[PDB]
Image (cartoon, rainbow, N blue to C red; front, side, top):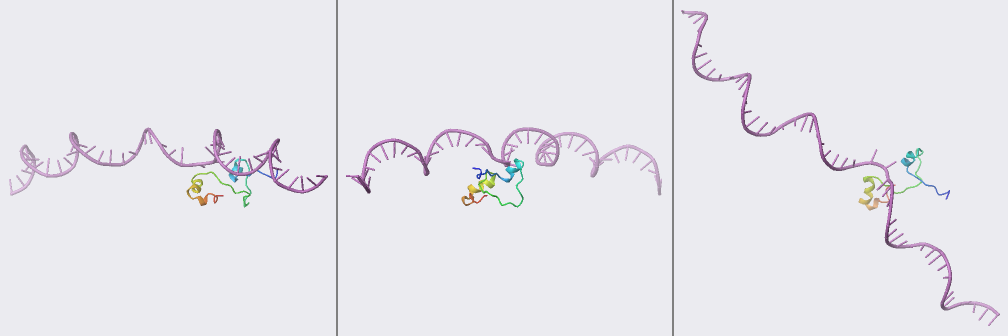
Amino acid sequence: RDCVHTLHSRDTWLKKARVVRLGEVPYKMVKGFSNRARKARLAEPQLREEND
DNA sequence: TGGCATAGATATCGCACGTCTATTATCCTCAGCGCAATCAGCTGTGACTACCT
């Protein structure tokens, strides 16, 4: 489990008093919950897994 | 005596049900712009009077 780390979004780390290092490739890509950018996935199902 | 069909005990993963929290928009109300019938000051009309011949 120590190899299993809990990953959070860049702004989540900012809320957690941490800064994501600039230019880093995101280790994990998950779905997000947002405004209309979120619902665009529902509007076009092909974009449901496209939003990273 | 020896190998394997078959009955018993034990979980086990897939599928569905009950529940929660997200990390950046919408809806009443006021001061400032308008449209429609009178009324006073500008303008037009009639009369009084100084001035010239």
